Each structure stands twice: as structure tokens, then as C-alpha cells.
Image (cartoon, one colour):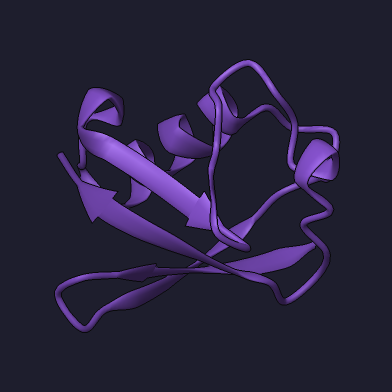
Amino acid sequence: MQIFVKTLTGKTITLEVEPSDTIENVKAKIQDKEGIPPDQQRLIFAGKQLEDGRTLSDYNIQKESTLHLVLR
């Protein structure tokens, strides 16, 4: 499924992911696409900071959802 990741620079990128993917995997995908190191990535959805070892499904992230990416 497609999701959106809205960064603080004005850029929103798209990713192809599965709800069973871990947050760590998603951060690795963001690194692949945009070059941002995972340890700098703070991901937020529905007021919650996302934890590396959990999955997208754990946070009820569905198709066409938007995550917020803030850099540490």
C-alpha cells in the first residue's frame, strides 16, 4: 500500500509498504529514498511517536495515511 511521509521542509514523499512492516524497515526505506539516516528520524502518527520494533499495523496505519517526519 501507498503511504505519505510529510517532512518539515515542505516535501512529502510516498512509500510502498505493508502493514506488517516494522517501523525500523520504514525508516530504512526513507533512508534509501531520501538519504536521511534512521537515527535522525522521529516518525509521528496520530499523536504518537513510532517505535522501531513495532509494526505499521500496531498503530492502525492504513492505506494513504500520512506520517510526519521530524529530524532530531
